[PDB]
Length: 219
Length: 219
Image 1 (cartoon, rainbow over the protein chains, first blue to last red):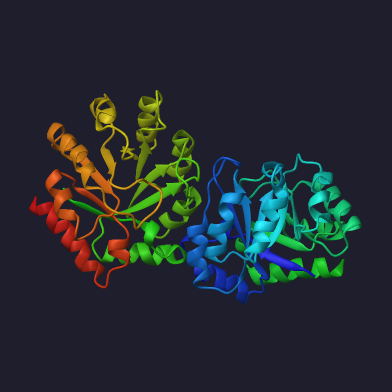
Image 2 (cartoon, rainbow over the protein chains, first blue to last red; image 1 turned 180 degrees about the vertical axis):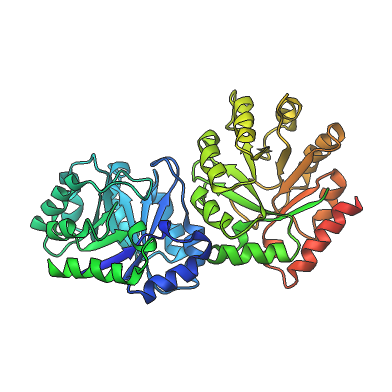
């Protein structure tokens, strides 16, 4: 099923609760929260304290993407904060992804795994096929760290490979998604769409959300 | 001169613009922004993207405290974001402190340096005495990372030492400051007061801010 998730990194961080309400009001399915620690990626955004404050104001699904070096140390804080989805990077969980997925699920959060552009898609197959698997795979379509970057079409091959092997798996894409890039992504098989500037910078955000949904549903 | 700086780490992160404005209306001189990267301290809070959005909603002095391992990489982003004060930790700015101070000042921000409880106060004397010196020294009165911890009276010896040598230097304290601990800190010589839970958790925050200011001015 299609899930449109505005990237709050592109919203007014100073009026988060209002922005969250506005997005839900405009049709958003989830709110994508980019958590960066300045180490895994060269940018620092928000952490669990922000998620906790936001949860007090909304019941919306908070899709948290951990671009941090030590995701295991965020499981407890984010679960307490009220995170709904917890997506970690495959590049920093090579020795403990099994326990990490289990620890996330134990806390009632939906486990997901993300991969940077340079990481071969085959690396996440074991995580999708595990006894306790990830329930979402996030294919980054730009090098993670900043919004406003150029969509990388070559990443659609990863989306396609995943959709072919796993027809019911939630496949998310993040990086340059918007009206001009949604069709190729929807055709490739992506059903969860993270978009920032294309939604918040639009004259009609609600129309953009609907257009993204329609493209996915059309595929 | 006394400066009262509420610690936004204790505020409603989902209504930052409103909280900042409320603090200013209640008499806050500066807004203390704790930037933690999960590495220098075991917590991740907010980064330049949050500061940038807040600046669009306030003209208040944003006193940013960098509890990160690589402060040099935040100078440009925070300057663009509108930070007013940029305080780095002496424990991670080694051999690069002279350049760091110059880079901060070169970008229109006020340079400051902070020291954890375990760090001898003598460590910062050269920075205060340099040709292009720090303009504020932040004596942590709790181990940095979280709000609500117990004030450490023993840290007042650092404050006193600094005040004795530098009569006009801004000396800031952060950690457990409130009505019950301000007199001993004001007597020691601290004039810039960072307080979180004692202000955001108070029935009369305006009265608390005034009391903190009165204590400092009384000294």
